[PDB]
Image (cartoon, rainbow over all chains, first blue to last red; front, side):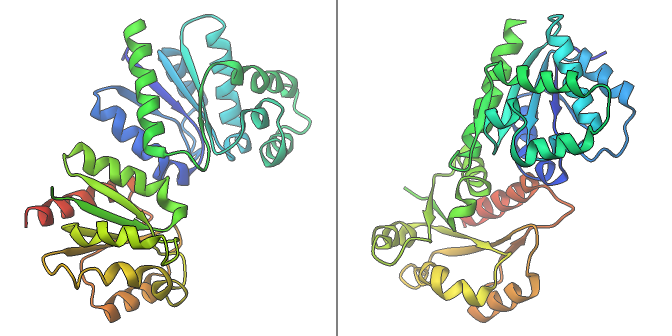
Amino acid sequence: PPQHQVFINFRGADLRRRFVSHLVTALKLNNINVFIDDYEDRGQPLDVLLKRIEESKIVLAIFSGNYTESVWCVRELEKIKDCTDEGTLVAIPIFYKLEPSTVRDLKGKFGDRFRSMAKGDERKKKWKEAFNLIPNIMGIIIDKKSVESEKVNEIVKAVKTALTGI
Amino acid sequence: EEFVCISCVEEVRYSFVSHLSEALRRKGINNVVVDVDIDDLLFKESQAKIEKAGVSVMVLPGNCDPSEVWLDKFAKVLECQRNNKDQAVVSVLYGDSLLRDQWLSELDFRGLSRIHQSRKECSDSILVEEIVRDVYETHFY
């Protein structure tokens, strides 16, 4: 098992090819071991993902507009939330081009996709509370006036700090 | 001393181009970013910077119609290569839905050949890498 692992949790092939590709290049540059999420839901087994998350020390939860279309991604967040409550990992919420309140209160396009995917599902309530609580962890914001390269450096800094602290 | 000038529209200024500028900077290559969405009035300061740049990098909005974009925004950047004949020009067609042929045609008409393109198979990070290597080779050239 690897044990200076950073888990990068998110969805979107466009996000993987763009912003995340730079974040990944900067982490590797700093010899930090990272695990990339199944961003296409190309069907890596859910138990493998949830286990990788548990084996991590850091999780970067990158909330984008596509996060709530995936039942598996939402299950990952639940697992994130469960693990932080047992104290086995540092979680850092990243808000990619949406406001945190949008996430917390499941507003707009973000929540509409969530409500559509979770219609008539028993676990809906528990999921709703996770989205309400994870954005209270300190976290990092990226809006359209943000200099992305600076935000990448800011995230890498937070990761270095968290890793020395463990 | 010697430096590189990146030209682009505003939509990419804070995303793709910032990564591009950061990458050059890590490699020890000084650079400045010029926004071409500015009209010819404030642009008069930026003309100065482009002219003394050794390498001028044009990051084009490849999803857009070149006929609706070239003359309006980038003609003025290319026209700085006249004053400095030592200056080399690098062109980047950036975008997730390129009007690839329209732009290749435009670039040919203006006489530009040193060209990089967005591809669905490569990340923007790889694209940045390819451009930094080209610039570096041209930078001491």
